[PDB]
Image 1 (cartoon, rainbow, N blue to C red):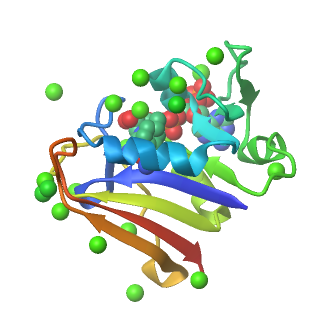
Image 2: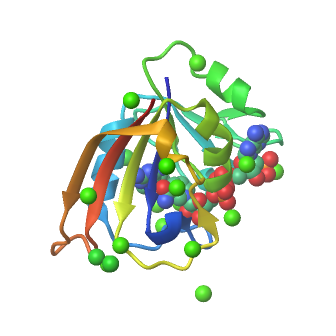
Length: 159
Ligand SMILES: NC(=O)C1=CN([C@@H]2O[C@H](COP(=O)(O)OP(=O)(O)OC[C@H]3O[C@@H](n4cnc5c(N)ncnc54)[C@H](OP(=O)(O)O)[C@@H]3O)[C@@H](O)[C@H]2O)C=CC1
Ligand SMILES: C[C@H]1CCc2nc(N)nc(N)c2C1
Ligand SMILES: [Ca+2]
Ligand SMILES: [Ca+2]
Ligand SMILES: [Ca+2]
Ligand SMILES: [Ca+2]
Ligand SMILES: [Ca+2]
Ligand SMILES: [Ca+2]
Ligand SMILES: [Ca+2]
Ligand SMILES: [Ca+2]
Ligand SMILES: [Ca+2]
Ligand SMILES: [Ca+2]
Ligand SMILES: [Ca+2]
Ligand SMILES: [Ca+2]
Ligand SMILES: [Ca+2]
Ligand SMILES: [Ca+2]
Ligand SMILES: [Ca+2]
Ligand SMILES: [Ca+2]
Ligand SMILES: [Ca+2]
Ligand SMILES: [Cl-]
Ligand SMILES: [Cl-]
Ligand SMILES: [Cl-]
């Protein structure tokens, strides 16, 4: 079971110059809660951005080139990334944009944080077909002292 997990602002913008330009710690707790104790697959650009392997998660990095860090598992293809996970109840694909595009047809579930933020981006989440996905969880939250925007946690399962 391959899942994609991502945070989308207005117009599916997910990043700008290798950062996620919003202040929303509620998404960080949601991300941690939903990925802990599960293998995480990421692209090289996302890996370089975090700088350290995510604890309590096998970290699988996609790159066409040989790996440069033995603390993580390096892979050269989508199918080799999935194989590297072994038999686990759930695999989490955590970004970035190019990795989401390739894994989307292979995913069975999407965990989306819809952020009410106007952001200029250079990275977008893929344009998934609404008819192919069913929302099975949808929780809206207003902004507060810690979270600068209103947001919604959504779980969609492939029909
Ligand atoms: N909002 C959110 O939810 C998230 C947003 N982001 C954002 O996304 C952006 C980064 O995304 P993006 O620029 O698309 O880059 P990615 O992080 O998706 O990484 C791209 C690199 O991954 C490697 N790769 C991808 N596919 C394959 C493949 N099939 N086989 C072998 N290697 C592959 C390549 O590395 P190589 O060139 O070495 O071959 C490629 O250059 C940043 O702005 C980041 O902040 C990231 C995570 C979450
Ligand atoms: C590096 C982490 C930071 C926060 C985050 N949040 C969600 N909802 N999905 C993700 N893939 C990520 C990537
Ligand atoms: Ca746009
Ligand atoms: Ca600028
Ligand atoms: Ca950032
Ligand atoms: Ca990042
Ligand atoms: Ca950091
Ligand atoms: Ca470490
Ligand atoms: Ca980390
Ligand atoms: Ca490279
Ligand atoms: Ca597997
Ligand atoms: Ca693509
Ligand atoms: Ca909005
Ligand atoms: Ca806002
Ligand atoms: Ca782009
Ligand atoms: Ca869409
Ligand atoms: Ca439709
Ligand atoms: Ca809502
Ligand atoms: Ca369904
Ligand atoms: Cl952590
Ligand atoms: Cl807004
Ligand atoms: Cl808002």
